[PDB]
RNA sequence: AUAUUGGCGAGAGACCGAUAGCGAACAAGUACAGUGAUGGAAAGAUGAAAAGAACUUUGAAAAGAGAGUGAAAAAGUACGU
RNA sequence: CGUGGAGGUCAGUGACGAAGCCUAGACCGUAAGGUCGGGUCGAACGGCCUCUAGUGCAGAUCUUGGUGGUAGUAGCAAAUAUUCAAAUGAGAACUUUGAAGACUGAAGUGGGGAAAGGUUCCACGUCAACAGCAGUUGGACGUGGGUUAGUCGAUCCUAAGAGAUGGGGAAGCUCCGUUUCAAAGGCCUGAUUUUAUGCAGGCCACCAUCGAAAGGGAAUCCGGUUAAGAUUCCGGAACCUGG
RNA sequence: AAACUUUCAACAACGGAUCUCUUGGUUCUCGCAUCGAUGAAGAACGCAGCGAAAUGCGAUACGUAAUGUGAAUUGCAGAAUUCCGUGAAUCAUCGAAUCUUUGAACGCACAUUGCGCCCCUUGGUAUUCCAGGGGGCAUGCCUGUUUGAGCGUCAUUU
């Protein structure tokens, strides 16, 4: 949150034959005079800096979720879907594939 | 001649080296230092000067004593010595 | 090469004392020689050998002082435990542990009784 | 060296903290020689240089190659 | 009162803050008295204090300090609490008697602001709380 | 400004609100903590019931 | 400055020993990436400000 | 139980990828500026390996031309593309 | 249409050459774009369904960097002035020696210093850069060398001032005050002669300190010497202070 | 018709975009509580066989001791015998030390490597002068010790 803004830069005002973007003060170094803060400016702060309190997680209705995984299960039993989904089951005995509880 | 020619007269120091912080910032007449505050009991530093602070705080130096304190504590401030093994 | 810590620990105060002067003298010797000659790594090890002697000399001297102080209430601050300015002036386990008479009497009578539910 | 082969002066880089008295004593004890006069100056590179004239009882060029250098 | 320690009365700002002469310190004179002897005897610990006398010019306080290095205290179970590092200069933080008064700390409706601590209750009720599944 | 036929909102964000924003990323994190401390309290409290 | 102080005088001596070309064998060190002394000084291009 | 843009030790990311990301991926709060408070940069990439071009020739030299190294010199410490 | 990143899938392309870049070569699309060949390259990278955004530039006297025309152009004209020859060198209008012609004309272009610089001093080597032509020269580059004190200064003193202390203000950073409403000592010295050191006469004392390399102030001169130091070294001749 | 201008192309330049890299940055989370008068943070000057830096160190100076590991370090040098060993190492760990001049900074000062005082000791005729060596003298406050002040004030000699 402090990136781009670690300057004491100011606009030089107009009348100086340069754009009014804030510029770095002092002399002695190539940073002196350069454009400061702001998105067009090399070094400056980015447009609308990314924040953490962005919404990351999404709420979903418990029942939609359930509905969701239920259809998802019902689908695991459709040879057309499981093949199209890219699994190789061209050769499995049957589907749903049940296997001895020894497993 | 408020410019070039009066610059020719600039040969008297306002500031010498400061005993405490080292900078040529020791005001001769005021007998004090603009960067570190010496000979104040305290060290000069303001909160509107995050860069200033950052430049001088702990860790920018050698940390002669303080560096080792972390390890010491890890081993519980051990008294004694290691003991030597077998064969 | 160069002396060894244990070889020196057997020696006597005044033996070590002379050991040292024998070393300063050879160091002086190599300084002069270093001049007329390109590169003298030999000098490294006496420089350190001098360190090793002085170290051990002091282990002794300190230990002595440390010993003739055993069991006495005020040791020097040199030999006192360092720790931490805080940890130093923290209450001793004794002081820490002091309970009031009223509370001695109370903790004995009604201590935290271990117990369990089910039956 | 020319101040030895002509002047009877030993030229030592001495400690920065050592004074003229202290130079005299150590030059006597380390070399078993007698000191007439000690001059000292702080070389521009931070080291101190002592100019030590010995008495006519001694020949500095002797006790020099005695020391070792030449 | 506390005369606003400002240049020539000059406030340089809105006319509300343009006062100099009728402003009162938010700590008791007693709080001042404690803190000043507490600074002088900084090896001690300020336990408490009490008024004893006053004229028009002055008020007078007796201040009860307590040595925390003195083993009579360190061994006294009723008082070794003040030996702790956590009580260094309790007067300077408003932890003495006069302090928790001025600091406005008691239960009940009258102390809604200040009792969980003025600035703290503020900062609380001035915080946006954002959960992962937004509420 | 004021326009259209909309409810009159009262969103109090005129105060450097950004300085005091608390997002609970550690919701997961402090649940685990909350447990790894109930089990570890149950351990030392012997057969007592917490 | 004619009769200087010792503090200055020392600061000077330091500064002069600092002023020298890179010890050339350093360039032979493994993984060395220093090809010159980028802190070299000169009495007429930069002052020492006491 | 609560706080925690500091300190020490860790595990991470639908973050940035050298004009981006901290000012600083580098002898960066350095070089430099200013009486002072303060201001404050630029600057990463030969090759797996220096095998960093022996030798000859032209030249006052720097270098050129051959030769040689290398998978490559359409990689020659001006050096990936 | 296109871009960075994400889930899924083509068991997708690839050192037998990924990506990238070059190409008045080819094809597809109204277009955003897509595909291919040839050259260059050298370690990665696509298509389709979906997710996501720091997602598309000609402009903002926009930001950083890089490059043009201007242009071999403006210009390199203050401060009297140069010339012959030898040497050296790969090389000489410019370096060194020699000669000539001249200037500064002691109110200096002479001989020293204060402030300031900090090695620029001196020697040897030496020309990539710098000295706005040049360079074999240099306050440049490289490597070395060099600054010697009882008497010269600082150090002592007081100046305008600066500023601890007992205090008195101030929420506090601190402000005031300097003999200040303060119990503010340091010396003569015999005793004792278990001892060189308690004691016994005792006067004296509105008293920190810092502040002058031009003010005040104890004392050195001549000759000789170095590549470069000298009222500092040598030689001789003195003087002050303390004991 | 050259030259010149312009356009395209190849090769060569200039410049450093593109692509691919990444011991860095950035944000999230988890565990922990340890600076200082036992002189901290920070500052100055030094310290290597050959170092200007960065890094590390402090006159025992890129380190001394202790412990682990077990043969390096490496630009060159040099070692080193210790390579079935109390033992390489610019290793790791670290419990013993050293730790210049400073800094809250403490005898007084400080644009000064300026100026005092005390004890022990060593030289020079020396209890008094000089020099060398070692150890010392800040302030506020608390508890205690010793020595004191006040017709503040008690009791006594007689
Ligand atoms: Mg940025
Ligand atoms: Mg003037
Ligand atoms: Mg002035
Ligand atoms: Mg101070
Ligand atoms: Mg002298
Ligand atoms: Mg105001
Ligand atoms: Mg208002
Ligand atoms: Mg109001
Ligand atoms: Mg209380
Ligand atoms: Mg309220
Ligand atoms: Mg709100
Ligand atoms: Mg508003
Ligand atoms: Mg948080
Ligand atoms: Mg519970
Ligand atoms: Mg002078
Ligand atoms: Mg100049
Ligand atoms: Mg500098
Ligand atoms: Mg870590
Ligand atoms: Mg950057
Ligand atoms: Mg850019
Ligand atoms: Mg930058
Ligand atoms: Mg500025
Ligand atoms: Mg590369
Ligand atoms: Mg590159
Ligand atoms: Mg060639
Ligand atoms: Mg190739
Ligand atoms: Mg290549
Ligand atoms: Mg080459
Ligand atoms: Mg699309
Ligand atoms: Mg598409
Ligand atoms: Mg995409
Ligand atoms: Mg992106
Ligand atoms: Mg084209
Ligand atoms: Mg390709
Ligand atoms: Mg590759
Ligand atoms: Mg999509
Ligand atoms: Mg954008
Ligand atoms: Mg553009
Ligand atoms: Mg445009
Ligand atoms: Mg031309
Ligand atoms: Mg012209
Ligand atoms: Mg003109
Ligand atoms: Mg002229
Ligand atoms: Mg001629
Ligand atoms: Mg001419
Ligand atoms: Mg004339
Ligand atoms: Mg005249
Ligand atoms: Mg020359
Ligand atoms: Mg030129
Ligand atoms: Mg030229
Ligand atoms: Mg030179
Ligand atoms: Mg004052
Ligand atoms: Mg004075
Ligand atoms: Mg005089
Ligand atoms: Mg003469
Ligand atoms: Mg006399
Ligand atoms: Mg090309
Ligand atoms: Mg890239
Ligand atoms: Mg990361
Ligand atoms: Mg210092
Ligand atoms: Mg064996
Ligand atoms: Mg030592
Ligand atoms: Mg002081
Ligand atoms: Mg001193
Ligand atoms: Mg001694
Ligand atoms: Mg008392
Ligand atoms: Zn300072």
Image: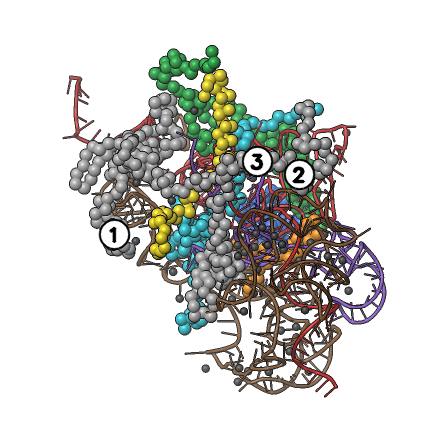
Chain colours: B cyan, C green, D blue, F yellow, G orange, H purple, I brown, J red
Chain letter for the residue marked with disc 3 in the picture: A
Per the image, label 1 sits on a secondary structure element best described as helix
Can you identify the residue that label 1 sits on?
E16
Residue I30: image x %, image y %? Answer: 62, 65
Can you identify the residue that label 2 sits on?
A82
Q: Nearer the viewer, mark 2 or mark 1?
A: 2
Residue A56 or C94: which is nearer the viewer? A56
A67, above or below J3, in the image: above
Residue J82: image x %, image y %? Answer: 75, 32
Residue A61: image x %, image y %? Answer: 49, 37
Can you identify the residue that label 3 sits on?
A69
Which residue is at 72% across, 32% downward?
A: A93
Quadrant for ligand 41 reads: bottom right
Dot 2 or dot 3: first in sequence order is: 3
Which residue is at 48% across, 46% downward?
A: A54
Residue C14 visible in the current orientation: yes
Q: CA distance from mark 3 to mark 1?
A: 65 Å
In the image, taking residue E77 as reference, residue D55 lies left or right, namely: right
| Mark 2 touches mark 1? (CB < 8 Å) | no
Which residue is at 27% across, 34% downward?
A: E109
User: Mark 1: is the Cβ under 8 angstroms from ligand 8?
Assistant: yes
């Amino acid at each position: 949150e402090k990136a781009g803004h670690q300057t004491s830069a100011e606009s030089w005002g107009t009348g100086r034959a340069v754009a009014r973007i804030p510029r770095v003060g002092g002399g002695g170094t190539g940073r002196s005079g350069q454009g400061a803060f702001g998105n067009m400016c090399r070094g400056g702060r980015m447009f609308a800096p990314t924040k953490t309190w962005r919404k990351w997680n999404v709420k979903v209705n418990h029942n939609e979720k359930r509905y969701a995984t239920a259809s998802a299960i019902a689908a695991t039993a459709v040879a057309s879907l499981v093949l199209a989904r890219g699994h190789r089951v061209e050769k499995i005995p049957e589907i749903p594939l049940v296997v001895s509880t020894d497993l | 001649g408020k410019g070039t020619p009066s610059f020719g007269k600039r040969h008297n120091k306002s500031h010498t080296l400061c005993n405490r912080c080292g900078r040529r910032s020791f005001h001769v007449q005021k007998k004090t230092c603009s960067s570190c505050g010496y000979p104040a009991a305290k060290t000069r530093s303001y909160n509107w000067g995050a860069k200033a602070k950052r430049r001088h705080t702990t860790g920018t130096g050698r940390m002669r004593y303080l560096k080792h304190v972390s390890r010491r504590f890890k081993n519980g401030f051990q008294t004694g010595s290691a003991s030597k093994a077998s064969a | 090469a160069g002396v060894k810590a244990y070889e020196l620990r057997t020696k006597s105060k005044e033996q070590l004392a002379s050991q040292l002067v024998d070393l300063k003298k050879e160091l002086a010797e190599l300084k002069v020689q270093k001049l007329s000659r390109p590169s003298l790594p030999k000098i490294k090890t006496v420089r350190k050998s001098i360190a090793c002697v002085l170290t051990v000399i002091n282990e002794q001297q300190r230990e002595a002082v440390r010993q003739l102080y055993k069991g006495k209430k005020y040791q020097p601050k040199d030999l006192r435990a360092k720790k931490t300015r805080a940890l130093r002036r923290a209450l001793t386990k004794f002081e820490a542990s002091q309970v009031t008479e009223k509370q001695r009497k109370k903790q004995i009578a009604f201590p935290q009784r271990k117990y369990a539910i089910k039956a | 060296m020319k101040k030895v082969e002509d002047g009877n002066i030993l030229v030592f880089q001495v400690s920065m903290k050592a004074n003229k008295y202290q130079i005299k004593k150590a030059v006597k004890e380390l070399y078993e020689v007698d000191v007439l006069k000690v001059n000292t100056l702080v070389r521009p590179n931070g080291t101190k240089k002592a100019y030590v004239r010995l008495t006519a009882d001694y020949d500095a060029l002797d006790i020099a190659n005695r020391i070792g250098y030449i | 009162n506390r005369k606003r320690p400002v240049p020539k009365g000059a406030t340089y700002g809105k006319p509300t803050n343009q006062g100099v002469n009728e402003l009162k310190y938010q700590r008791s004179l007693r709080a001042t008295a404690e803190e000043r002897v507490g600074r002088r005897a900084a090896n001690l610990r300020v336990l408490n204090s009490y008024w004893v006398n006053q004229d028009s010019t002055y008020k007078y306080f007796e201040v009860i300090l307590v040595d925390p290095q003195h083993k009579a205290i360190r061994r006294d179970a009723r008082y070794n609490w003040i030996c702790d590092p956590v009580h260094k200069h309790r007067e300077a933080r408003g932890l003495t008697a006069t302090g928790k008064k001025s600091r406005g700390i008691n239960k009940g409706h009258k102390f809604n602001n200040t009792k969980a601590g003025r600035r703290k209750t503020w900062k609380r009720q001035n915080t946006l709380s954002l959960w992962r599944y937004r509420k | 400004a004021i326009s259209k036929n909309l409810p009159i909102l009262k969103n109090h964000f005129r105060k450097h609100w950004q300085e005091r924003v608390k997002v609970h990323f550690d919701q997961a994190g402090k649940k685990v903590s909350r447990r790894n401390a109930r089990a570890t309290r149950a351990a030392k409290i012997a057969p007592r019931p917490l | 400055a004619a009769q200087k102080s010792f503090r200055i005088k020392q600061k000077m001596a330091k500064a002069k020993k600092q002023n020298r070309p890179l010890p050339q064998w350093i360039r032979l060190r493994t993984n060395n990436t220093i090809r010159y002394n980028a802190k070299r000084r000169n009495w007429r291009r930069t002052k020492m400000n006491i």
